[PDB]
Image (cartoon, rainbow over the protein chains, first blue to last red):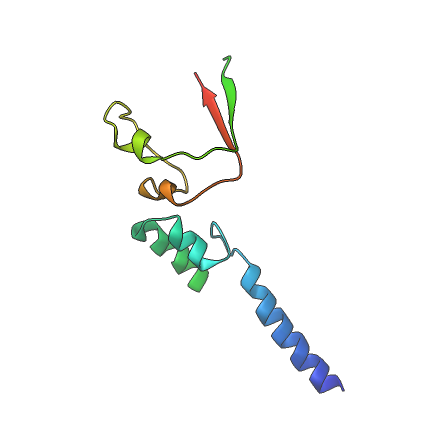
Length: 50
Length: 50
């Protein structure tokens, strides 16, 4: 059971990492790409991708 | 020293008028693109005047 438990935990934390800002204005990328021009959305998306 | 605070809510606007008009010259927005405030829309808006 413990290997399944570990794999589910790893995927769970990987998915949950998506809701994270990581120093950006908003976690969801389409938001920041919709409320910014390309020149600064580039910086925000760059931090998110990093 | 006595700034006035006014509400904006339950209303529809067109942020084109303020931006494009040359009367308002000094323009700068922190975290929001100017041309895009036509499509971005906000829960409540606070206007401080002085």
